[PDB]
Image (cartoon, rainbow, N blue to C red; front, top):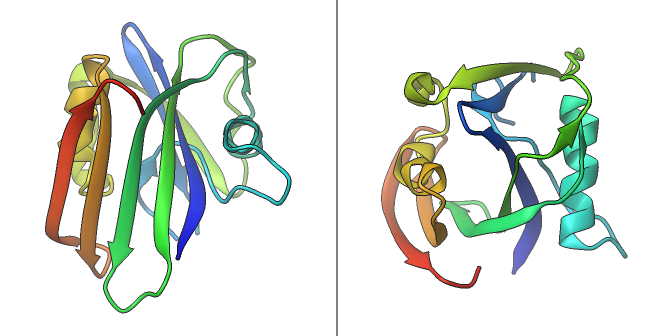
Length: 153
């Protein structure tokens, strides 16, 4: 029914790393992630995708949320497991696929991100954990959604 995905926010006390995809989600800033592979844990997939997409090596990951995405007329629900970290090693690498950039917390480019980010980023920035569901029509319109803070992701 649903397909496992990861999403990793490198969130430091004064800045967050985002990445701009050159070609799904192209032209938007987003966290780093993708599909989880066979025999791979969700956390291991999060570590892998962060390195593949940003060049960074993450030490400890922390689960901060789970977000299910529905795109009307698409059979697969995206079950996105959201992680946060402050302990990274390396420098963000720009590749032909991905352009990383640090943003000050007051300057997060919400107009150039997936529209769901405006809803749950304020929770992530105050260190709250959450479960969410977003129903999209196309890539730009949220038809409906639910979002609640949780003690256990």
